[PDB]
Image 1 (cartoon, rainbow over the protein chains, first blue to last red):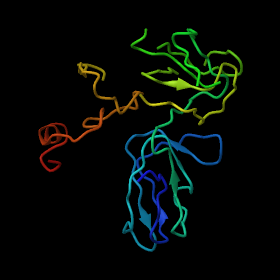
Image 2 (image 1 turned 120 degrees about the vertical axis):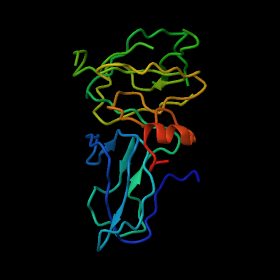
Image 3 (image 1 turned 60 degrees about the vertical axis):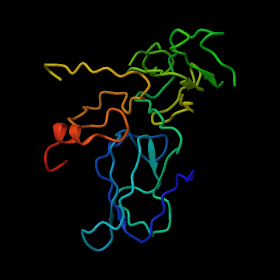
Image 4 (image 1 turned 135 degrees about the vertical axis):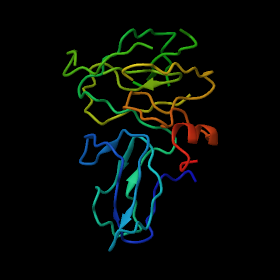
Amino acid sequence: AAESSIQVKNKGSIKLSNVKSVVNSSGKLVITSRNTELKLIDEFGRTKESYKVPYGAVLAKGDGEQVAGGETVANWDPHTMPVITEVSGFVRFTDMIDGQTITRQSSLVVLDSAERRPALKIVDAQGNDVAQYFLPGKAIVQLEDGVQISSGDTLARIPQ
Amino acid sequence: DGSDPYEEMIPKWRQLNVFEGERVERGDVISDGPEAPHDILRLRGVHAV
């Protein structure tokens, strides 16, 4: 099932447990905890549904909202888990080597461990120091330096 | 972990489920896969197993 949408059978209010609240670029929140639980409370304590929510997911409706049912309550990438930026501002890229750690597809790969992963924090505005960014194999960041990206946003990670 | 660190080695053929510290608790899934019952009771308990 390539579809990442989660359907709800009945109108039961979602009960998101074991989650971390992180402010995203919009009113929705992104969970940074690998272990998450969902539940349905409609009239009593019994939970109609459970399902599962991976890391980097965005909930369509907030916790405690009585969803009418038959509609998506949380949406996430079914192929990749996005990495949330703790600091909002320009992306600080350190030791950017062109021709070895750059792969044109702007969208450019960060680095390759086999070919060689510098760690740096997101700049506050342009280059201020405020967080460790880890780049595993085949990790790509499409946001160039000075993009001034807000918190809770992520580019395509390109899993290895 | 304050004291007595857990030096564990992975052959790198297995991906790491978590990247940050996240205050990982005992029995948490560091890497994904079907877990053996020996580890469950060892890091969870008899009722868990």
